[PDB]
Image (cartoon, rainbow, N blue to C red):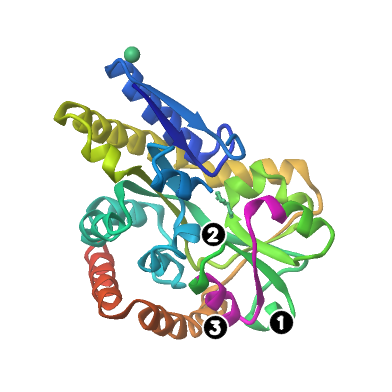
Amino acid sequence: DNWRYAHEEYEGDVQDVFAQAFKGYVEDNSDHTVQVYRFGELDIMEQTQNGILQFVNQSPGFTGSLIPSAQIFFIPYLMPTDMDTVLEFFDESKAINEMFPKLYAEHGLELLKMYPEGEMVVTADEPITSPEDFDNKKIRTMTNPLLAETYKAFGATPTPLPWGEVYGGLQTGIIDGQENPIFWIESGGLYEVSPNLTFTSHGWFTTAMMANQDFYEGLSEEDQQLVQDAADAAYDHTIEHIKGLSEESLEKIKAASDEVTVTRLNDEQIQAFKERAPQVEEKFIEMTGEQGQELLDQFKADLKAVQ
Ligand SMILES: CC1=N[C@H](C(=O)O)[C@@H](O)CN1
Ligand SMILES: [Mg+2]
């Protein structure tokens, strides 16, 4: 059988690294093939739900509209900063490994893996050392509601847009900045048009890979185990790939542009942004009810356990 798999990124990007590894495992261990569609190579979620696609990698930044609980990742300063700790969290969290698959199942998706890509970094037309610096800045967000609220809380004017629109928008001042992991900033050449990088440490770009649930459930026990085994292999490979990635990417950027500036928020400057976080958490709960409170409680507990 041929299994169609779509993701959000380009050749060599983090999602593609995961994809290619997944594909590789399946092909190496079965008679099956995985057909991977990169960005633009085809609404990938719609296409998965209606069964055109078997697998899809979509980030909560988008999925958060359809699956409100997925917005949890956009609560600033909830997630740790340390790669090692984040990795431990993803491996061991019941929120991630037990609860979220339940939540996705409600939408007819079989959540296979959630994984981090990189720490979020702000880019803009100036350094941003304080919420005040955000004032009257149109900052692009991915298209989920909580994420807009986050940026509003930070003092910006959130402008949610599809990825396709971002480079151009920056270039002609439709937007004043955006947020993304460094590897994407680099691979996407965003630094060319948004040269001031600020490390706010407010969170991580994360993503998820899943299967159409009917498809998955429709597979033989053997093929199910294959898929699981492949996801585990891809995860492992991808985690190895991201170690040192941000550091390499930043070097790449510095090599490419003399105009790039890097601002790293100190502990004091961080607390100021952190002051804005609780209001976002409150909104999250108002969006997701008791089910949401339960997830958040587990999330926080999980975090505590790895720290
Ligand atoms: C890191 C990443 N950023 C894009 C975005 O910000 O829209 C996503 O669409 C895909 N991957
Ligand atoms: Mg084969």
**Residue at the image point whose x is 74% and y is 52% from the top:** 167
Q: Quadrant of the N terminus?
A: top left
Q: Earlier in the sequence, mark 1 or mark 3?
A: 1
Q: Amino acid at mark 3?
A: Ala
**Residue at the image point whose x is 46% and y is 86% from the top:** 279
Q: Amino acid at mark 1?
A: Asp
**Residue at the image point whose x is 32% and y is 46% from the top:** 113
Q: Earlier in the sequence, mark 1 or mark 2?
A: 2
Residue situated in front as seen by the camera: 202 or 144: 144
Residue 71, image quadrant: bottom left
Q: Amino acid at mark 2?
A: Met
Residue 272 - label: 3
Q: How many numbered marks appear?
A: 3
Q: Position of residue 163 (x, y in %)?
A: 64, 53
List the residue tagged with mark 2.
120
Q: CA distance from mark 2 to mark 3?
A: 17 Å
* Residue 157 belongs to magenta span: yes
* Residue that sits furthest to the left in the current view: 221
Q: CA distance from mark 1 to mark 2?
A: 20 Å
Q: Position of residue 173 (x, y in %)?
A: 82, 64
Residue 135 - label: 1
Q: CA distance from mark 1 to mark 3?
A: 15 Å
Bounds of the magenta span? 147-166
Q: Earlier in the sequence, mark 2 or mark 3?
A: 2
Look at the numbered discs 1 and 3 and tell me whether their residues touch, using CB distance below 8 Å: no
Label 1: how many Cα within 10 Å (few below 14, some 14–19, many 20+): some
